[PDB]
Length: 119
Image 1 (cartoon, rainbow, N blue to C red):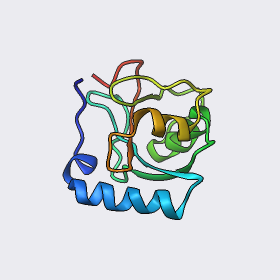
Image 2: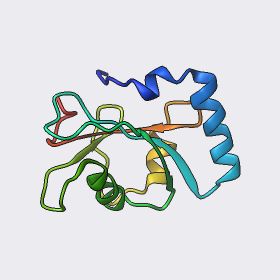
Image 3: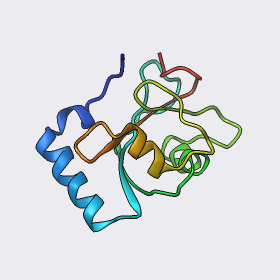
Image 4: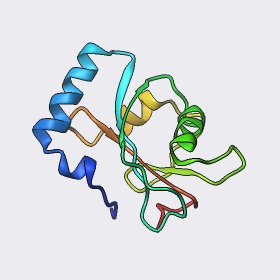
């Protein structure tokens, strides 16, 4: 592993957890996501990080939504990196959560302008 975070890193466990354990209970179809702008990424840095996206939302959909947050067109480059890996466009946000939720009932992710975790 070699991922760098600040919002998802700063927000204590009791926080990322408190929010998650609630967003999960309150929203069974949604998944608390902590998107991030991978290091060295040739894209704009995000100050939101938090994302309340559904659970059926495919990676392809999630992208298009983040692309705007960074100002990228479908043609533009933008790759998601969770736990330092790239999720399948066919996979659903809900899956990434259950398959990459780093505890705290949260799901943190990254995005770079390359096929590598920004770096």
